[PDB]
Amino acid sequence: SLTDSKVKNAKSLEKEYKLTDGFGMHLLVHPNGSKYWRLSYRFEKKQRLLALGVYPAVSLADARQRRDEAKKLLAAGIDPSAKKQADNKTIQEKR
Image (cartoon, rainbow, N blue to C red; front, side, top):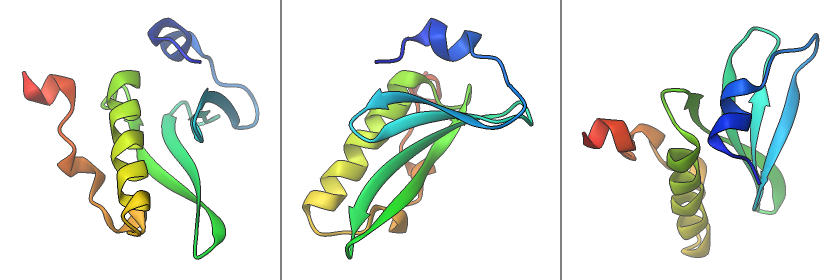
């Protein structure tokens, strides 16, 4: 399971790598320096990858919330790629 500090302190390498958080979610740490939240899921029923947002715009807590929302859509038979992820307000945006 990831922590805020592991996420913050992860450094880019030569090639992209994934830091897994569980339940299909990972942080992609890209050599471009950017950090992407992603969810692996199955639907229709191929394996797919969902973008959940960009750190630090989206925190680890925020990413887990967006994962949860995607799992709810999946459970209702809705492809979670149809969702505008930004409609999930972040904890800071809430402020």
